[PDB]
Image: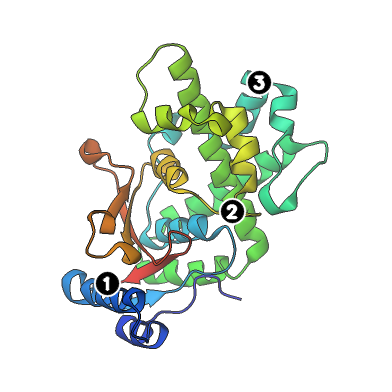
Amino acid sequence: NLSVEAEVDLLSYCAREWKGETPRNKLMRKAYEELFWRHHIKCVRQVRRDNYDALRSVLFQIFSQGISFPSWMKEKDIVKLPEKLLFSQGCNWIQQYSFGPEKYTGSNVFGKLRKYVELLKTQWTEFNGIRDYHKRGSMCNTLFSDAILEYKLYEALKFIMLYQVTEVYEQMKTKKVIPSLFRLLFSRETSSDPLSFMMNHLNSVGDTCGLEQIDMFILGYSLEVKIKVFRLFKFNSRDFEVCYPEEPLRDWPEISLLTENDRHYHIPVF
């Protein structure tokens, strides 16, 4: 039931899961050994459930570590963002949101977005007002054992990503300075504008694909969290340690994730 599986000793998992003599398996065991001895990661919580796994892993880290709302949410109310885009964007524009695996075609994308975004606001607020990490831990095991609620929070996060994509696109069109990552996003045909991004990429997250690397950048930027990732299959190479985004002069909160294939992001436990 629990989608962020119970912790297992890193060296045990490494020895049991990656037994063998192939060049790839040998490299994987060296990577995990590096994680243990150099970075003092003692255990691992596996996150391999569905195509929301990237969002599942990041959200788990935010709540478990007690990270609060990003700065731009201080002034803007989260629950009003669906209305703002309903207003700024077209009535048909917003009705094209499909809610990933729901493959929704009903008549109120607006009501659903507002409800789900409200649930994320409520849940996130509850975690912010708890200083004891243990209490947050048990709450996470409860939350991530309720897949129906999980999906609603993930679609809320996907909407927040879409909102930031729409904000930054408007900045680019009005000749404002924007992050090079967003300018890169809009250079791709299938994501040249927020509508294309939603229909061709975001609508698929959780249904047939997970978050791509560029999507991890958008998520971190949107939540103002530095997502540090150990890419184990790239051990002994430049991109073994990566951060989404690469905003050195940010002073944002930071979370760490482990991945063997850029598809599933396991939780490092110290």
Mark 2, residue position: 209
Amino acid type at circle 3 is Phe
Q: Earlier in the sequence, mark 3 or mark 2?
A: 3
Q: Earlier in the sequence, mark 3 or mark 1?
A: 1
Location of the C terminus by quadrant is: bottom left
Amino acid type at circle 1 is Ala
Report the residue at 64% width, 65% height from top.
147
Q: Earlier in the sequence, mark 1 or mark 2?
A: 1
Amino acid type at circle 2 is Cys
Nearer to the camera, 56 or 21: 21
Report the residue at 47% width, 64% height from top.
264
Mark 3 burial class by Cα count in 10 Å: few <14, some 14-19, many 20+? few
Mark 2 falls on what kind of element? Answer: loop
Image coordinates of residue 175 in percent, x first then y, are 41, 12
Q: Is residue 183 above or below residue 6?
A: above
Image coordinates of residue 78 in percent, x first then y, are 54, 37
Image coordinates of residue 4 in percent, x first then y, are 50, 71
Q: Is residue 50 visible?
A: yes
